[PDB]
Image 1 (tube, rainbow over the protein chains, first blue to last red):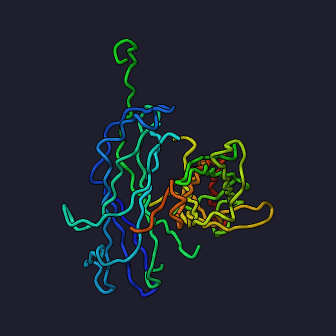
Image 2: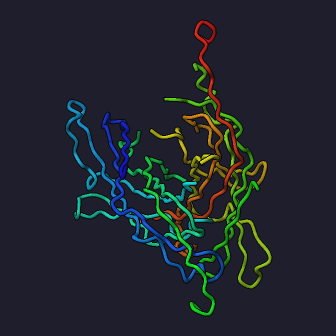
Image 3: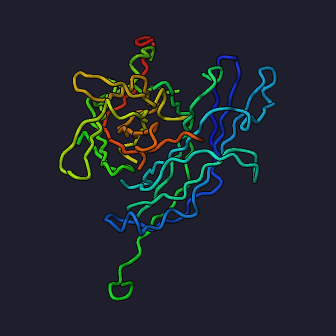
Length: 169
Length: 169
């Protein structure tokens, strides 16, 4: 349940598949609360969520064969994080740009190192992929933003540290 | 209840306030499933959100000045579906570009005419604003997307139409 994929067809008849895979799930976070200290003395979600993106060309004849064109496909990609209660709350920078790396896999990567949750509880992360196309053949303000697909994280727990006035000081 | 505001400070020391307010709440939709009335599926009436941007000088932080037509940046509004009682559930085009209009008010406007819900139930819409900055001094993969704020809609009902063979085809 770490991955999700979507497919679309371009004007040139090309079948493009987007695959999102969460490689580093969140596990825990300390509720940062509100106030002036909440924006400068917080502990972000750890380990930072990391999402891998792959793009596949499918030749029209044989669909058992795909070609990873992640390093060839020319478009802007952004990944946006939302906080879904399992039963603003999310602070920080919820938008990550793509970084193309060869290890551990040849793909694009999104990292979220500065996510904070305001209140304790159980949450899931939803990561939404936006594509900004620069070649008109790839099509399905003079720039457009297209939602592509979404991946759902495993549940993680935000705890609250108990208060001990004379102890923590 | 239909609006939300968020303030930031640019590099010049000016305070910039973004205000999102919903002009047309969603009311009803017919579950689209995976029933020959297909224009009955898009959420109706199409949700409409207006955006206003206000400038406050560091010398006077108590007064605001609308700069919605002056602020040089691209804007996008992204719709997410929130279950009021917590293959995609939301379908269509969930990204709306901004349109600058003078009537009914001089502001930016987003319209969502092509949103569909797969399952019946009570839902809410969350609209997230993304700012694509073109002027570097307005600042707080060469292009970047910045999240600003979200506005949450009133609950709306998605209903299902029963099948009566020999009566409803």
